[PDB]
Length: 500
Ligand SMILES: *[C@@H]1O[C@H](CO)[C@@H](O[C@@H]2O[C@H](CO)[C@@H](O[C@@H]3O[C@H](CO)[C@@H](O)[C@H](O[C@H]4O[C@H](CO)[C@@H](O)[C@H](O)[C@@H]4O[C@H]4O[C@H](CO)[C@@H](O)[C@H](O)[C@@H]4O[C@H]4O[C@H](CO)[C@@H](O)[C@H](O)[C@@H]4O)[C@@H]3O)[C@H](O)[C@H]2NC(C)=O)[C@H](O)[C@H]1NC(C)=O
Ligand SMILES: *Cc1cc2c(nc3c(=O)[nH]c(=O)nc-3n2C[C@H](O)[C@H](O)[C@H](O)COP(=O)(O)OP(=O)(O)OC[C@H]2O[C@@H](n3cnc4c(N)ncnc43)[C@H](O)[C@@H]2O)c(*)c1C
Ligand SMILES: COc1ccc(C[C@H]2c3cc(O)c(OC)cc3CCN2C)cc1O
Ligand SMILES: *[C@@H]1O[C@H](CO)[C@@H](O)[C@H](O)[C@H]1NC(C)=O
Image (cartoon, rainbow, N blue to C red; front, side, top):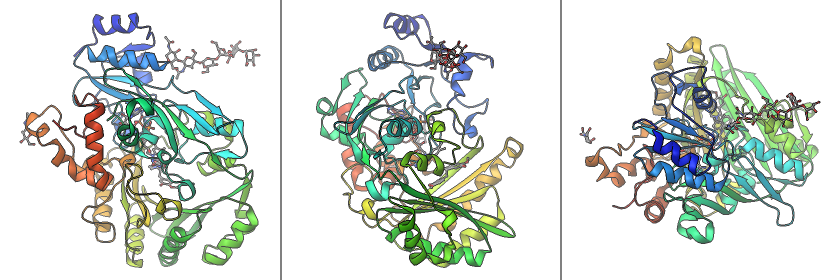
């Protein structure tokens, strides 16, 4: 379905002047803006789905009207903030679709009196973090480490980061927000009601409508926090020992502490990158690990004291705090597919050993280990759609990324990742095998919203990944879905089905 004169005239009429139409060209602005926020080259392929038009609204009413104009046609709506969807569900779709890029909605309004902020859904974590440190040295916010990840889909799915052990997810700290429904109705928390305002805070993106802006509570942070990023080159024996003890240390640390691990291997050596964050000074930080985790062999020089801003930039591997404010800094430029696990029981050494052995078989693979507990276990499972709280111990994350040179090995890389996930099945959560909506996994299945045979059973088919992402909260998400989008205008392969 083309993007005809009706759609365009509708946009022109409504003052939404920033938009381009599909172009087979490569030198075109369309293709440029399209590939501008494709954060997973896995989907840069010339055979993937491409929008009939890309619209870049610059205000909440332009956003409202954009949705209104698209509703006059049959197009599927696709919202994009940072475009970091692991499945590229913000710039792809089986059916002809319109791409609503929210990058022009990147304003952060910080209020130092209430210590809250109105973050436009276009604003990325980085641009947000920058705004906060630009305004205060005693304020921060909890969310992912990826500075290019947009708050649009990030906070919509939850938002887990290095401070979540201290403050919970991003969505755990949303006090208000502006959602724009299928009719372009501009709704605040009071207008949308509690069932929906609850849903949008971890229920997923591209499901409830277009978040125009988030109102977050800004969080206290000492003017000096401590972090370390130390890569240990060890053998598999030591690596297992370190990982096996890590899970306990990491999960049982005080909320003022976060210890995350990035593991990979290559035949000979196993490399474990230790990412440390302390909600306080260096001496206390080092004292703690010197006691709890002396095996890391971390030294004084390893611990860096810096502002909270400097720390989230440092942790993200950025050169400077200014780079937090750069939304177009690709952090790898490599295609990838990532599966995640959540643990209820501790993991046997054999699990880390197996993981490390499997890793040593494929250098392009690597695991990310995150501890829960602390503040994550104090927030109710039903406080927000994100269920995994008290009881959840670790977030294990299996990634595999490659170069354009290695595009041929594609299927092989995915094969490895499939083998690793299968290998971990006994050691992780079961019935259901839990997942995280911001780590959306189309392998868990999907829904063909064009197939009425399936659409009639959308809720049960969706159960597979639904209870996996949201567990018991899945029920309330369906009531909330029916209230704000019964027509299922906002959908994607793993969107919450409305009651029909
Ligand atoms: C649809 O949405 C898309 C996405 O948002 C829009 O595309 C964006 O369009 C932006 C402009 O509208 C564009 O910003 C540009 O970014 C470049 C860097 O790539 C930047 O250099 C440009 O900024 C200059 O120009 C603007 C005005 O055009 C000035 O306000 C600004 O101060 C900059 O001018 C200064 O630097 C220039 C060289 O960098 C000098 O030539 C100029 O003289 C001036 O220098 C003075 O100021 C300096 C610093 O203050 C000082 O050192 C010096 O001595 C002088 O005093 C430009 O803004 C984005 O690149 C683009 N974004 C993307 C992702 O493509 C698009 O516009 C929308 N479409 C529609 C229809 O609206
Ligand atoms: C690329 C990348 C992803 C990361 C990174 N680090 C993460 C981390 O530290 N913790 C995590 O929890 N997740 C991490 N991820 C994955 C991201 O969390 C997810 O990819 C988030 O969805 C990020 O959102 P965004 O960058 O905006 O991706 P989009 O593709 O634009 O959107 C995702 C999803 O949400 C819908 N959507 C977008 N915008 C809106 C608005 N404003 N309103 C409602 N819904 C919206 C889209 O349709 C899409 O379906 C580290 C890196 C490098
Ligand atoms: C501190 O905790 C973590 C640290 C790093 C990661 C991996 C990171 C990533 C880093 C890459 O370089 C990359 O290459 C394509 C892909 C990805 C996919 C997931 N993304 C989030 C996950 C974590 O949970
Ligand atoms: C509709 O869904 C069912 C179940 O997946 C499938 O068997 C059938 O082929 C689908 N029909 C269409 C329209 O493709």
